[PDB]
Amino acid sequence: DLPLDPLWEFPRDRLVLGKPLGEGCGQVVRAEAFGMDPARPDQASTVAVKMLKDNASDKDLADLVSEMEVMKLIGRHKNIINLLGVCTQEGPLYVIVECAAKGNLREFLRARRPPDLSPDGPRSSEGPLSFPVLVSCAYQVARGMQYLESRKCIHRDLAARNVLVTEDNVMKIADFGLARGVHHIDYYKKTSNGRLPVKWMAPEALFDEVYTHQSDVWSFGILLWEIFTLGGSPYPGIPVEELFSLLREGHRMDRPPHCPPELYGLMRECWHAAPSQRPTFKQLVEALDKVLLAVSEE
Ligand SMILES: C=CC(=O)N1CCN(CCCn2c(=O)c(-c3c(Cl)c(OC)cc(OC)c3Cl)cc3cnc(NC)nc32)CC1
């Protein structure tokens, strides 16, 4: 059956599968792994494991294998979900990646929105989220995307919900190696979560089925809006039908409340019609870095 890759192959009996982590289009499971670091063979670690759905066609198998091989080639970076190991021999196909304890960025932000709350303590009107951390989140997603771009990897669905947050609040770009079938997209279809993925698509991607890294930049611009709305849904109260014509008329989202003009400027820059007139991820990393270092250091 599948070829043995000793560099990545991990003994399946060293896995202890646990509770699911989400939906997927295979099954994702939180698992316990022993000896992932071969220097510490009896040391436990929490990982994420992707497997095949019950009654999976040969396509579902080919998709996961394809996704497995993409992650091998892209390599390691602190701001993406990294491949840890695989199980290809003598049993079902397992793909083992890093686990993000705090879930996706959208839920992270929404669950940490600021407080008519009865004031206790010295910091009652002080929410968990502060401006510099928000910028840091944006900066990390940018650096992560930059790495992917350098690996000639286009995400095609960059969004706050496709960014994962670790125990130490590190942003990791999720699901970057998926074959999402961009020729059969139901633009009207609303996900289980209530999301309309069409709201993250660049015009050249939506209208012309053209994806580039500049297409991801457009998406990143939408992600920027999500961050500083603390998990707000883009184009509020606009159904897909209206979004079509609005985008054709060149409509853009308004400046969100409590958002400095520097960042709304970057958003609008990412939403420039001409892809060449949008910033690169390298420029985004640099721009966001300047804002990050401009914080008051007491
Ligand atoms: C697409 C529709 C959908 O409805 N959904 C539900 C939400 N979404 C679940 C997040 C659960 N989840 C993953 O899918 C992965 C993960 C990632 Cl990103 C990979 O990218 C390359 C690859 C991979 O296998 C190869 C795994 Cl297994 C890693 C991961 C780490 N941590 C956590 N904790 C919540 N959850 C993860 C999966 C997509």
Image (cartoon, rainbow, N blue to C red):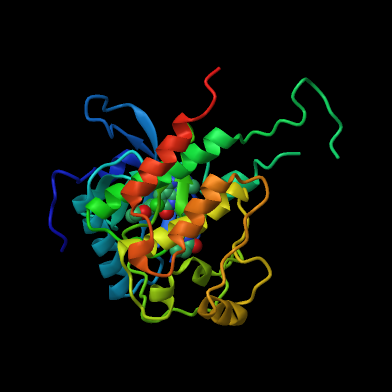
Task: State which quarter of the image contains the N terminus.
Answer: bottom left
Please, is residue 292 above or below residue 214 in the view? above
Residue sitting at x 64%, y 33%? 128
Residue 42 location, x and y as percent?
Answer: 31, 26
The residue closer to the viewer here, 246 or 166, is 246
In which quarter of the view is residue 156 placed? bottom left
The one of 221 and 63 positioned closer to us in this rendering:
221
Q: Is residue 148 above or below residue 277?
A: above
Rendered location of residue 288, percent (x, y): 43, 41
Residue 29 in view here: no
Residue 107 in the image, given as x and y percentages of width and height = 59, 49
Q: Give the left or right position of residue 191, taking residue 44 as reference.
A: right
User: Who's the residue at 76% across and 39% down the image?
Assistant: 115
Dividing the image into four quarters, tell me where ligand 1 lies.
Answer: bottom left
Q: The C terminus is located in which quarter?
A: top right
| Residue ID at (43%, 76%) | 206
Can residue 270 be seen in this snapshot? yes
Left or right: 85 in relation to 103: left
Q: Residue furthest top?
A: 298
Q: Is residue 173 above or below residue 289?
A: below
The count of marks equals 0
**In the image, residue 280 lies at what x, y percent?**
33, 54
